[PDB]
Picture: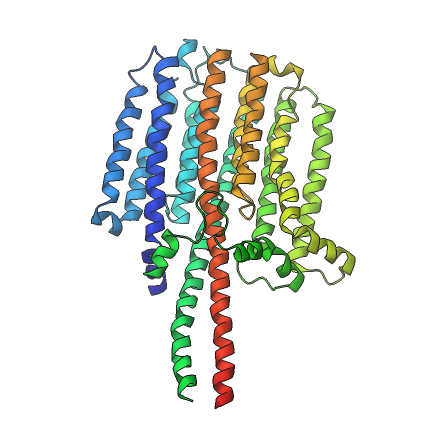
Length: 482
């Protein structure tokens, strides 16, 4: 329990820094999310533009509260207070909006549901059990208010049979968000705690070395560690070149050395869970897309069916490789182990990872056809599904954040290019830009932070082993003299 209180005490500056950036993001979000609310929904500024301006000062008021000493004792309470306020406004926002100029597309609200639910799982530093329920609470209240308060005048009501299976669409996407959300939370908590123990062991060995050195001869840093990392701020590469090459190769030798898996922070175990979500994020997302056609009794295109077989098989092979990489079945031959050594390399992981991460992303865009403009529900469903495909790019934290989220930006630009070619249509096109730009900003920030945390975890590991090896070298010399 004392190590628990110490850990929150030592990593409090990280919690404070992340919280301030969420304060900047929400205020920055409300600045541009409400400008187009004021302009493109000019008929009703009474109910929509006012709350956003009010909450902007609340974010500033929260921002001012951060510098006070009372914040440090109840940083958890402050996050919960912000979470309820952010939960309430955006949840109640999807209600007051619901004549064509007064209706907001079902994609715009979903982006608010994503960024809000990704500040909770990543930045509020709220307990997992309460974060999961609040995240689900913001999800069930999001879906169960749109159905209640749907405006049939703006969006024509589809078939009754289609509505029931479309509930799976609302549920399954929200589930994907939480599955990414919990994993994003779990890995952040694991890497922060594992680094703390490694720094705790590193400082412990440093003091122990001096006691040993004296016997042989006779015969605040951790705060700056979490605040001033040994990493350049732009490219996120390590300042030391020998460490950077060590980090880039750090994955393969552990595969070569068959290092046993001890905790979730192991790169092989991290990749196994990382590849695992990619399959479920694919399997749940692609399940959602296909059930739309069954509800509309229109056969799916064979090309979309064709990519799925290649996509699932690639997921099946990649998943099977990871389990064999972690558990090492005894009947593996040396030829495949060399291949297992090869994929573990830095560039091979990026080439494989880029395919693995982008796989649910290309799943959504394989269903786009020339009939994309026939039904108005198809683009709003594709846009809603495209958001999570971009959201999936926060996974695979071992890859470079620049490489991953840029593919998300490329993938996030897929629907945009479709809309420009197709071009209420003009108004939605601008909304989707604001939908994704705010969303792509979050993935840019979130991927940057978690690569830093992942890189610091490795940096904490080598410093722990560098100091630990110094202990064994000195102990052998010390006992030899004895």
